[PDB]
Structure formats: C-alpha cells, structure tokens
Image (cartoon, rainbow over all chains, first blue to last red; front, side, top):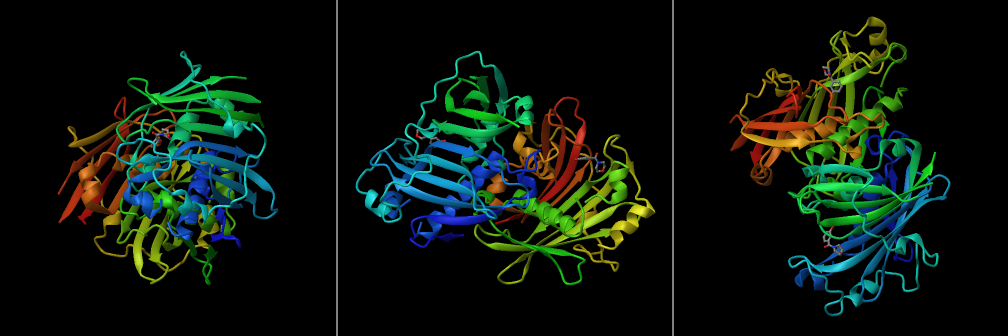
Length: 262
Length: 265
Ligand SMILES: O=C(c1cccc(O)c1)N1CCOCC1
Ligand SMILES: O=C(c1cccc(O)c1)N1CCOCC1
C-alpha cells in the first residue's frame, strides 16, 4: 500500500481470499468493510499515527455512521484497489471516504463514506474540538471538498427512523466471541454489520444482492452484552433495521439496506 | 503465491492485518488457521484442482478434515510478513495429510508448524470410505514420494489420542451459534469457527496471562447452520493444559474434542 503523489490519500490492493467469499464466490459486504478498515489503519500509519494532543486528553475517534454502496462484489482471486481519504467537517467531526476499483479494468465497483465523532475514552462523552486539534489534521486532508457521495441530499446523509414493534423478522440472542473483538477487547464495527444482516430472510440473501447499507452506531455492545437483530421490509427490496440489547431493549444501532434482484 | 521449483509444495506470503490481531497486537490462532486454509486452497488451484480429483467429482466424494494440529512458537505481529509453505502426502487407503511450515519473512526462522488428517466422504450420504487406487494415482503426482513430515518426532503430539471430557465440566460457554460470516462459499460452517468455539470456554485469566502454544482438534460431526453448540473445558495440568468438548446444546451429541497447551507469558 502507499500514499498517492500529493500525499493526501492512500491506495492499497487486496487479493480476495477463499474464506472471504459467500455462495456467489464473491466478497461478502463484511469482508469489504474489513478491507475499508484495514486501508484506513494503513493510511493513519503512513502519515505518522489520534493526535498526541487528544492522546493526553484521553480523546478517541469513534464511528457515528457507516454507508456502503457496492455495484460489483470482487470475485475470489480478483484484485481490488481501494483509495481512502479523510476530511474535516468543522467542529462536528471528521469524514473518511473510500473508492473501490477493479484492478484489471480501472472501473469503480464500490464507494463508501463514514462520519467520525470525538469521544472521551473513559467518560464516553462527546467533545467536538476541546482545543485546536483541527490544525493537526488539516495537513493530511485535501482542503478542497472531495466527496465519494457528492449528489445533493444523497443516501449517505438520510435520516433513519426507529423500527416499531412488532418486527417483521428477527434473529435473537446474538453474542460476540473473541474473534469479534479488536486489539483493545472492543467489538469490531464490522460485527454490527453482520448482526444487522442476520435478521434478513435467507430467501432474500439467495435471490438478491446487497447494493446499499447505511448504519448508525448509537451505543457500544460490550463483550458480555446480548443482541437482538430486527428487520422490517419498507418497499428492488428495502429494509429497516434495529439492533438492541436482548434484555432491556436499549438501542445499540439502526440502519437500512437496499437489495437488487439477481 | 507460487509452487516451489520441484512443483511438489506451495509457498505464499501474508501481511498481518489490523483486524487479524488480538490484545498482544499479534495474529490470533484463528487468523493463522484461516491463512493455512487459504494457502491450501491456492496450492490446489495452482496444480489444476477446482481439491477433488476427476473421479471424486463423478462419485460425489469430497475430502473432509478429521483432525487439525497447530503449534505456534511466535505469533506474527500486526504489519509483519509471514511465509507459509504447504504440501500434501497420501497415507495409503486411510486418506491424505496436508502439512504447513510458518516462517518469519525477514529472518527465515520457523515460527510455527501444522498438520491435518483428511478422510474421503460421500457428499450426500455422509459415509466415510477408504481411498481407491484410481483416485490415489491422480494426486500422487502432486505429492513428494519420500516422507516429508512437519512433525517427524517419535512420540509427537499430532498423533495423540484425545479422550472424552466427563461432566461436570470445569468451565463452559453455552448457546454458541454460527452467523453468515461463519459460513464458507457452500453454506457450511468454516473449520476455523470450531477452533474459536473451543477457545470460548477458556477463562479470560488464562488468555490474558498465557500464550496458546499447541492445539489439536478432532472433527467428529458437522455443526449445521441451525444447530446450537456448547463449549466445555477442564484443566488437565509454568504450563497449563486443557481438555475440550464441543457438543449440540440439546441432546449433547459430540461435534468436536480437543486439547490446548498454554505457556505463561
Ligand atoms: O456511544 C457511541 C459509541 C461509542 C463506542 C462504540 C460504539 O459502537 C458507539 N456512539 C454514540 C454517538 O456517537 C457515535 C457512536
Ligand atoms: O463427520 C465428519 C465431518 C464432516 C464434515 C464436517 C465436519 O466438521 C465433520 N467427519 C467424519 C469423521 O472424520 C472427520 C470428518
């Protein structure tokens, strides 16, 4: 992987692995989201990385929202190239965008965007800026707007409502295993995407392809928490999703999916 | 990745990924087992397979894992490059064996080794059968003919008999179930998921203060997509030893048994 000529974005190539594909022998949306996270980590690493300013303040970047649109899922053995960049959005937070491409043809096979907010790692309270952490970041971001989803009032910025009971479909009693944890013993953001899709009926998965997925992160699922995945058809097939704690029904995530008939 | 000069083994390099590491910022045993499976699939692909022979596809016969054995000396760190060499060898009518050697790409030192026993099973009836001569000759050409063992030792751990855990279990993780991410391209639970489920019943105190050195796992019965699993563990022992049992949450039907060896950090 490497930073581009201007040093303001990062590109990396990935060979699709045998255990990374589904029934269609193409990459799952969860494999894709893992590769977005990987090329994001390598981008931060290549530019010197959270800044030392927020390291002392005990401030961390946390995902508020993930949005992913796939046109073609890379096949097993194919090479996919992902380009990623970050950009400030004022005091609100930061945005990381991605573009997925076919390595052989150069065509765009997918695109993704994510909204990141600042949080005190201990108190879990949001702080927005605290002092002047903007200046530390602006040097590694393009200063002119560079959007993976430029369309005025696009899908990535749509408000998602709360699913009302009774849910049409459900997957209950879902719980993380050690493989679902990151290097800090926190549940991986991609696990929540898997849990959302568990309540999608197999008939849909087998006859449709997942085109769009938007997910709002509201609360962290702990290692000892149990999750319930709810889904209701809103319609191509459209769905409304809700992940909540199995006990008190405390919301952890909400989202929408768009599926295209094969 | 590529076949070696003699064309009788395959090598591939892997950069350890950020989401592939644990608390120590080194590759999990599950990430390692996924890479053993990947370099195995690429070896079959490079020699013409799509790893069933012409005769096996005709007879609805498939290769199935009977046992996996893995020994790790050093877990590759996040960002490190690990090189894995794999080869297959027939063991007469019993079946075949696939072995692996993991190495540090920068120093060339051996950081791990693994072996697995594969048996032939009819895809539809789930009935095992010995390897016929016509199938045997089809894959003998892709195997070294002189013995090449990742575990050559006389009283080696890779071939030790594993007993059945007796209730009450000392530790337990109950109600474990596969999600879509745990399935392969044929909607069958991935062999690595069973390794994860075995380790779920290991107390966190052990995971945090010890490193997993050896793991041997016998595959007895396939966990279906709608099955629920219970993970049991009992300490058998500077080193900690464990006895494992994975069984169906309902009737207690055995799906796997195994042992782990942990060394204090
Ligand atoms: O409280 C969290 C959060 C914190 C850590 C992990 C997690 O999945 C969620 N958030 C509320 C709004 O801001 C973004 C998400
Ligand atoms: O019953 C199985 C089996 C089959 C498929 C998957 C699985 O996890 C186990 N076997 C017969 C005995 O030898 C080992 C293989």
